[PDB]
Length: 62
DNA sequence: TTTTTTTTTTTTGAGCGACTGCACTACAACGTTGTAGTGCAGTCGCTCTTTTTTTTGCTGGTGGTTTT
Image 1: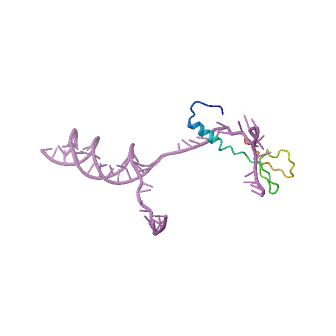
Image 2: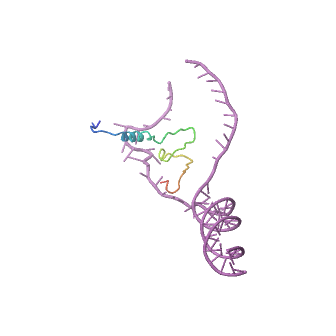
Image 3: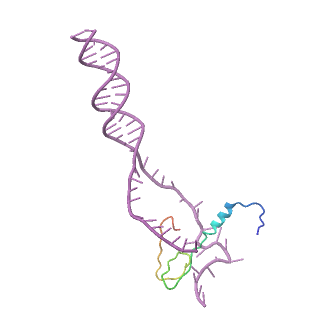
């Protein structure tokens, strides 16, 4: 799409394909049936009754 | 294009340095012999650490799992 004319080696395309195969995004699906195990972002202000916070040691969070 | 069998483990330390025994000549004590010093070879102890250091995009943004 940029109309590149010069030669492109193998390692650049190999690293670009390796970067696009490990781009699996963190799932934010919520199921109302079972208890939801998830990270902080998906529900920021949703008002649940019981709220548990794991992994609150130094270095990891924030 | 088809198809057969099968239950037995092995090996691994070597260089450095001392202990002890026998041979071998030099030299003084009593021509010959006993004591002393060294060379070479078989046998044997011993001994060979300690450790840790990191950036990676939570959903960076037309994004988003699941039913007929």
